[PDB]
Image 1 (cartoon, rainbow, N blue to C red):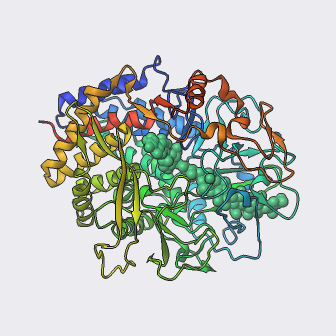
Image 2 (image 1 turned 120 degrees about the vertical axis):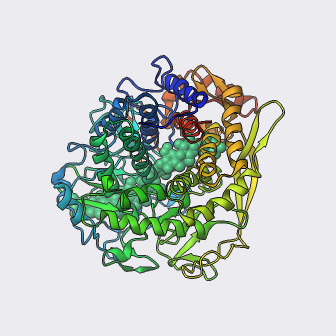
Image 3 (image 1 turned 90 degrees about the horizontal axis):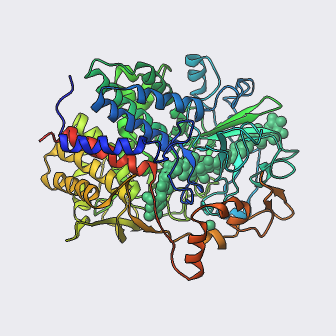
Length: 629
Ligand SMILES: OC[C@H]1O[C@@H](O[C@H]2[C@H](O)[C@@H](O)[C@H](S[C@H]3[C@H](O)[C@@H](O)[C@H](O[C@H]4[C@H](O)[C@@H](O)[C@H](S[C@H]5[C@H](O)[C@@H](O)[C@H](O[C@H]6[C@H](O)[C@@H](O)[C@H](S[C@H]7[C@H](O)[C@@H](O)[C@H](O[C@H]8[C@H](O)[C@@H](O)[C@H](S[C@H]9[C@H](O)[C@@H](O)[C@H](O)O[C@@H]9CO)O[C@@H]8CO)O[C@@H]7CO)O[C@@H]6CO)O[C@@H]5CO)O[C@@H]4CO)O[C@@H]3CO)O[C@@H]2CO)[C@H](O)[C@@H](O)[C@@H]1S
Ligand SMILES: [Ca+2]
């Protein structure tokens, strides 16, 4: 039987769940897939509001798990897994096993350099550069009896707004797409959206392929997908709680547990350097697990031929603290119901749990905020790490891993998303390493929450960094990183971040007994409920400071390359963001946005992001369970 919950906060969960699931609110497509946001005029990581992301799907899982806990009905949670498998994990038709079975674990992919400006792409493939061996592929094909990968592709054009359709048909929905391809300076404003399945039917002469990669011959027809490890790890996290909550009530989500466990087994590909080079010795090809950093890196990716049979897989050399999930790693390595089938699945996750906790502590600043991360591939070309750069297992510190436009660690949101998982681990296990991190981090952030007399509040929004951590010595441990400092640049009322913050502080308070954390969590939740509720969930008006880029951002197109988007928009040198997305001019908010820009005003919007609404709902449910009085 489930323990009693605080009825006030349970009712607030239940209300939010109804608003989110309400067909009249429009959070979901007709196929039952959640959109990034209700509103369509939306550019921030996805560049259209009615895409879906693996991030949104994993929040949909967490939301439904919590509904199961309060309602006793887990059919919604099982359905969230069904929708995921149907639409976001590429099927047999989307990643033909005929190509995947031709994968060569001794030569997983061909090296190409990354560049610091999009104008340097296409990047030339070089077969002479060393590439290491993949030691896990044989474990996976042996356990699961296929060469297909079981992981979510990160983004889906749910209603076929771009027009690529499914497997180049132009008409089916949903449509697998990707955007980012051209390194750290390619913002969301500078991409050329492209189909995952490229049969050269759209775009240029060879579809979109030769915008990004240059090979010897004629570009082949080919598919490719990219994982977002932080989403797949959150799926495992959510499913663990669904299982716990289901078993407290004599119910079962065993089917979904098997899917989560399998996903966690494939998620190990994010543990490896991009081209399986040795960690801390990047000039050398790895021999297997010497190429594993055991962190959740920015991606893994795979692809292969459509009309001939070959395939490739890469991990990623770049690691951000924001992606780590020690809770998921604890689950997969210790809980017998979530032990992966592969021979080394559980022990690899055990190593990852230890490595991840070291990583957070290495990056913890003097004040307590967590700095960016590290890379095994300096400048994305395995260049020499400058003398004086601090290192973690031979990987050089990077202040803003992977993206510089804007810096990937200049947003406060990464702090809460990631420390929330450390707080669950600490709540569940009392782990000393987690305690130490949280004591200092929570003390930092409790000093940065500002409550106003009118019931409104502010928390950090944009942050900046000085210095670097001390070189990590696993036997010395944490030095205090006296020369690493966070700066709060501005404050805001980001409701998704405030919700995640409330969640983190609630788990931490429950375990540590810290009253200041508990009351800050409740005050945030109350302020949001009382002051920001609307008929669709919660919202506030926000400034969209980068929206001038709709009209003024030039998109790079190589000299002489011309093509067309499916709607006929011409792609050629000179185009702006809006020129290759001309359907955006039909958006109900377009004229409002343009009028603002014409007057030299910053446009504002009131946005209902699926992840933020779910975050708020889950944060209420968490407080209700942990603080029943
Ligand atoms: O012999 C036969 C045959 O051979 C052929 O040759 C072959 C050869 O054999 C073969 O080896 C090679 S393989 C080659 C391949 O060809 C080539 O294509 C491939 O290239 C790869 C590149 O090397 C690699 O660099 C790139 S990596 C890139 C990925 O592609 C891309 O998908 C990924 O995108 C990421 C994305 O960056 C990330 O964001 C997301 S997930 C999630 C985040 O986790 C989360 O933070 C974020 O949250 C958002 C939130 O949603 C928002 O609401 C908030 S908004 C917030 C504001 O930010 C605040 O400022 C504001 O104040 O408040 C607001 C409100 O809160 O913001 C947060 C934070 O941002 O959201 C997102 C989700 O929404 O994940 C994705 C996925 O990970 O990026 C990666 C890094 O850039 O990949 C390329 C592949 O795609 O390389 C291989 C090997 O080299 O191929 C040969 C040629 O074919 C011959 O050719 C033949 O002839 C013959 S027949
Ligand atoms: Ca740029």
